[PDB]
Image: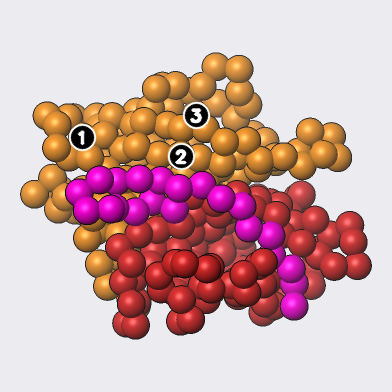
Chain colours: A orange, B red
Amino acid sequence: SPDMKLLAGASNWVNQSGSVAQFVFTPSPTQPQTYEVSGNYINNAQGTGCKGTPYPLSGAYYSGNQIISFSVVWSNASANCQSATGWTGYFDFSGSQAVLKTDWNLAFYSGSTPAIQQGQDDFMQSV
Amino acid sequence: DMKLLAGASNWVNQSGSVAQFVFTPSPTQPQTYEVSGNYINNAQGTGCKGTPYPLSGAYYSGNQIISFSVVWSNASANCQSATGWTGYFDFSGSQAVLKTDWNLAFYSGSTPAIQQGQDDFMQS
């Protein structure tokens, strides 16, 4: 049932930086056990751009073993950081509080030089 | 960078995997497109090769940066896993190249794992 609670709602998840992802799931019309991920992400990581306002997220979720991959392009009405982040990982519902474990890639430019930075985010569910 | 949006092109990686991207303007994000289309996997040693899987993601047109994902579930095979690619199009050379880093989340029995790699796709 933690699994179906996720599918029915808009759930919130806070990572170690204080940033917050809100996820909504819609069944795929062609892929079984698969959901289109929508929702928004608020970046609260110090030392970064594009903080404090929601950015849409998009991606896909596999309900069979609760694996997700989602992305944000850092462009909205408030700020544009000319970049995108992709997260891929898995939910763990085995503890008393649910956790989403992810690896991420941030593609961006520094002047004319492109780069892709790697990192890891652990999100803990908000109630 | 315009050829890319035009409609349908094939982007082929070092193993012969093929990404077929479709773009539609984002409802709320400036200079951004929703990405859809299909991915045909051919990565050596991997499951779910040789059939189209839908992909989804987002593309930033200002400097041609993309992030997209595939869940490995369709009517032909289910590998109970998902891959996310993030990277940038380099239109320097006579050959355009999409340079990406990817993560694959999967289970081995009861143990979850996330594997990393890199894929370079060339426009066919």
Of labels 2 and 1, earlier in sequence is 1
Amino acid marked by disc 1 = Ala
Using the numbered discs, state the Cα–Cα distance from disc 3 to disc 1 in whole angstroms. 20 Å
Using the numbered discs, state the Cα–Cα distance from disc 2 to disc 1 in whole angstroms. 17 Å
Residue in front for this viewpoint, A10 or B82: B82
State yes or no: discs 2 and 1 in contact (Cβ < 8 Å). Answer: no
Instruction: Give the residue number, with chain letter if any, for mark 1.
Output: A98
> In the image, which disc is placed on residue A43?
3
- Which portion, as a residue range, is magenta? B104-124
- Image quarter of the N terminus of chain B: bottom right
Q: Residue at x 22, y 53 (%)?
A: B109
| Within-10-Å neighbours for mark 3: few <14, some 14–19, many 20+ | many
| Within-10-Å neighbours for mark 2: few <14, some 14–19, many 20+ | many
Q: Residue at x 74, y 57 (%)?
A: B89
Residue B52 in percent (x, y) is at 47, 79
Q: From this view, report whether residue A36 is shown above or below residue B110.
A: below
Instruction: Give the residue number, with chain letter if any, for mark 2.
Output: A103
Q: From this view, report whether residue B120 is shown above or below residue B17.
A: above
Q: Residue at x 35, y 45 (%)?
A: B113
> In the image, which disc is placed on residue A69?
none
Point out the residue furthest to the front here: B45
Point out the residue furthest to the left here: A1
